[PDB]
Image (cartoon, rainbow over all chains, first blue to last red; front, top):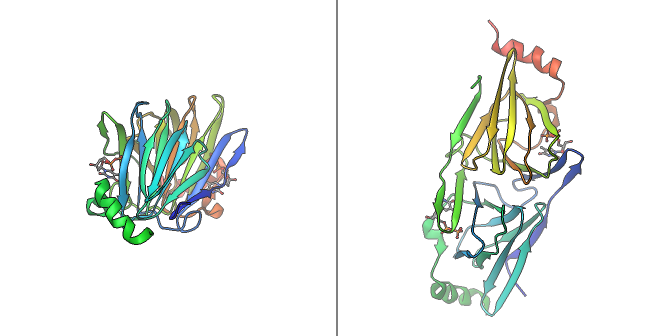
Length: 137
Length: 138
Ligand SMILES: Cc1cn([C@H]2C[C@H](O)[C@@H](COP(=O)(O)OP(=O)(O)O)O2)c(=O)[nH]c1=O
Ligand SMILES: Cc1cn([C@H]2C[C@H](O)[C@@H](COP(=O)(O)OP(=O)(O)O)O2)c(=O)[nH]c1=O
């Protein structure tokens, strides 16, 4: 099984006016929201991501259509489809992830605990594996 | 627009892999983000909203499809259509708004300066007007 990952369930307020989910920082997720970002209009043959973070905490949420997330740590690979706006996928440090099968109209929103910092990314898989092994085995 | 309202333009990092817009609190919007919420799956005939806030700062953003925002202060109305994920509509305190014409698959994201507080809502239009009149009138 897979360390440093959780699925977080949010409130979904649904009636004849539609659906509404609220997320309060440190309350419905464990961290303060310093930054958000969202991905839209990804062609269906694209795989995005391919990175890890040393310090950042993030929660991924698919608010329209569907997207699959491949999560890896050494010797373990999991795939989680996200297709319910009221479920968040929490990814801690040193998990490697990849996002693919973006459906038509898909919207991926990420909530993040720090401002964008290029030095906090690991983008080379061989460097990731090296660093992750020190933690995991 | 009106008083206390602005359209804000965000980075759209667009390439062969798609679009990505990042928003950092205090930086790309003028406040720190304590709460987000998002509305989805609204039927074509629904209007929602129907309120103002005294303290809350907010930024509205349509991430898919299209949705119209009706903004009111006393004796002035403007209608803004949201249809670009790279454009946010900032609404400050003492502005009444309603949301309507949510298209099929519309997603409306709201960034908010404070945690949900029902006492900061004004939900009755006449009360809204009485309070707002204080603010805006000579
Ligand atoms: C996530 C994010 C990316 N960017 C920029 C950094 C990169 O140059 C570019 C592409 O992001 P990248 O992290 O490579 O994409 P993904 O997670 O979708 O695979 O966007 C920001 O400026 N701010 C941000 O918050
Ligand atoms: C916005 C929001 C609403 N809610 C709850 C309380 C309200 O009764 C309901 C939201 O409806 P309301 O704000 O009245 O609707 P809209 O903005 O779409 O017109 O859900 C929260 O618990 N937290 C929140 O942040």
